[PDB]
Amino acid sequence: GEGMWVPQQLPEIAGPLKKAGLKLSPQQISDLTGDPMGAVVALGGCTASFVSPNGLVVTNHHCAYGAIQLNSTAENNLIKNGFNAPTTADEVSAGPNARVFVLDEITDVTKDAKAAIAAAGDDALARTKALEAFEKKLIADCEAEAGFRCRLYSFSGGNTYRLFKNLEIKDVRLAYAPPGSVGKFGGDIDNWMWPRHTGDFAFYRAYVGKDGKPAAFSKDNVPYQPKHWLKFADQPLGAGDFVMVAGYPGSTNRYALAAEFDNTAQWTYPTIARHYKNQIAMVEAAGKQNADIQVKYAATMAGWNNTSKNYDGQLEGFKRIDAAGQKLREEAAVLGWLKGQGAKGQPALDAHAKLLDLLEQSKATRDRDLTLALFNNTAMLGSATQLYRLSIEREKPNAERESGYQERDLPAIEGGLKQLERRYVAAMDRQLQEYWLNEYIKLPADQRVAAVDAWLGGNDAAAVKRALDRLAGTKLGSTEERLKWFAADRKAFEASNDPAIQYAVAVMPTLLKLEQERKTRAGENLAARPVYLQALADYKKSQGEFVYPDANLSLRITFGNVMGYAPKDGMEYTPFTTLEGVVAKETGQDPFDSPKALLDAVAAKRYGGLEDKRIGSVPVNYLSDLDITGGNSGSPVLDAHGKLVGLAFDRNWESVSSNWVFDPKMTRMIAVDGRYLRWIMQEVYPAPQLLKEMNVG
Ligand SMILES: CC(C)C[C@H](N)C(=O)N[C@@H](CCC(=O)O)C(=O)O
Ligand SMILES: [Zn+2]
Ligand SMILES: [Zn+2]
Ligand SMILES: [Zn+2]
């Protein structure tokens, strides 16, 4: 059911947990470094878990896609063919920015953080700077111990703050991925859909240095030895069974204002979705005629497709359940309720009006702000602006440098400059510059930027062509040139003839003021948001309701049962899909083109000892009433005894609106069964060494 529960709410949900079927004590689950929660890790945007004492990590194929794509070329395409390392020495690096974060400690710093903010007094921009200075000093102290990275989380709009300390594993390697025809069976046609028939899993291995401390890639590193790992279920998972997920959901907007909902639904989603579809259509065309572009843009294309399809789904979802109507009605009840406590409620109603003025200021420049951000996120312009901003921050002491630009951030910056090599083709990138210059032109001068106007030197197609031809002269298309500018000082940038660099130097002043503007609004948000949200929580508690914070990239627990749903009258989706259903979808062409060994093993009924007697076949995917969002991919699904019964990877079509307004009837998680993963690895694309390591072969 509904709820992304923080672990410190386990006491509250210990009862609901038992009634749903949890057989372990809630006590054992609240041990975040014990069995089995201590096996659960964060990847940065995905979840994973340890499944052997020698550092083997299981996650989704789509979470591993970036790493697999970084190790692919037109002639040796791992996305297409899969990868299997017979020995740990054949494992390839997942890239320099790949991480595994192992939770060590959590601390409440709420009082301290609130005191730091309070001291800034009644100046918005000063409140943001005071929180940033608090966070930096807190982080530098937490990170003093070698091999740990830390993170400060804000919950419920600033009402609670907790500090997470993680062991940061820095050498992560790809150990197995099934071919893409399994890992992403059905492609974008089946994405966000049930019925689903997709083997969305893959495996990494975590490595540390010989002294046991984390270190960057080296052939002298050895497997990490986790204190906790997961074991495969010994009991068959069936309809109605208890399941639970632990992982790192990124973002939900359930407690937002009705008008923030309106703005997202009416402007942000249709605008982003349109842009992504435009860029999809360009890069698809180039890739049909150029297999280098196709492989180098594949991870990017997977993201555009995923996000745009999500946004379409949410908009359909909003209509279906009248989300505008529900937000409007519930916000009346809340306002109504506060007005009837007079002076007690007054802080919260002031908070409310302030929030709407912050919304209006941001709406006033929405078009400029989105368009400029996305133009500056093309490869050469993103490189030049990032690298020049770094040269400006290098002139300050580390403690005053902007977050993203301190010493602790230098390894990610350098890594990203090298990964870029595998995701850039000059001719493709030129077309994307072109698209974004056309979108810039089509702003009213109302939403325009003095420095870009000046730098373009004209407002027409001729000006766009000139810009394109000017920027074609950059040297930043080579990794080595990027790395040179990575170490150069600000005067060197300022003297450069590189046309991408000159663009960065021309726009930087504007970019910093725009950033100052954002920090000012955020500083107002810091005063108003926590007051409003406390009062929203106080209201919900009056209605006797469930209370949990919106997702914010921290560790959450969701629980419930295996079950289908009814998409319309006369029909019901069943909880499981099966092998025969994979084959019934076969067309011989992308994306319904299973490997031949899958086709044969299913026509022969080679179930490998994995048949669930109740369904008469090996289960492939299953539905449940768990509550997940982006960031939960790769999370282990555990049964009543805390054993592994699958991996979370998607949500059904009708549920994706649940990010804003929850719908219990049609909100389900889609997971890949642990038996399908075993079956693929025994019968289709075999990896008997991994099966043996996990004590299932
Ligand atoms: C490439 C496809 C399978 C990605 C999924 N559609 C997806 O976005 N999955 C997310 C988890 C489910 C959710 O968003 O609610 C995710 O990647 O975290
Ligand atoms: Zn263990
Ligand atoms: Zn280096
Ligand atoms: Zn049988």
Image (cartoon, rainbow, N blue to C red):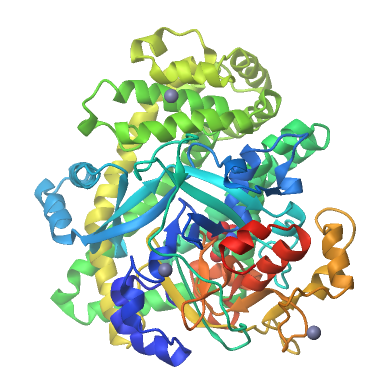
Q: Measured from the top left, where is residue 25 in percent x and y?
A: 35, 84
Choose top left, top right, bottom left or bottom right for residue 667: bottom right
Q: Is residue 222 visible?
A: yes
The quadrant of the picture showing ligand 4 is bottom right
Q: Is residue 268 left or right of residue 489?
A: right
Q: Is residue 194 above or below residue 39?
A: below
Q: Measured from the top left, where is residue 224 in percent x and y?
A: 43, 50
Residue furthest to the bottom: 19
Q: Measured from the top left, where is residue 413 in percent x and y?
A: 43, 32
Q: Quadrant of the C terminus?
A: bottom right
Choose top left, top right, bottom left or bottom right for residue 653: bottom right
Q: Is residue 492 above or below residue 11?
A: above
- Which of the pair 591/381 is nearer the observer? 591
Q: Is residue 477 left or right of residue 183?
A: left
Choose top left, top right, bottom left or bottom right for residue 321: bottom right
Q: Residue at x 19, y 74 (%)?
A: 345
| Number of marks drawn | 0
- Which of the pair 63/205 is nearer the observer? 205
Q: Is residue 648 left or right of residue 494?
A: right
Q: Measured from the top left, where is residue 342 in percent x and y?
A: 17, 78
Q: Is residue 673 visible?
A: no
- Which of the pair 172/630 is nearer the observer? 172
Q: Is residue 570 above or below residue 464?
A: below
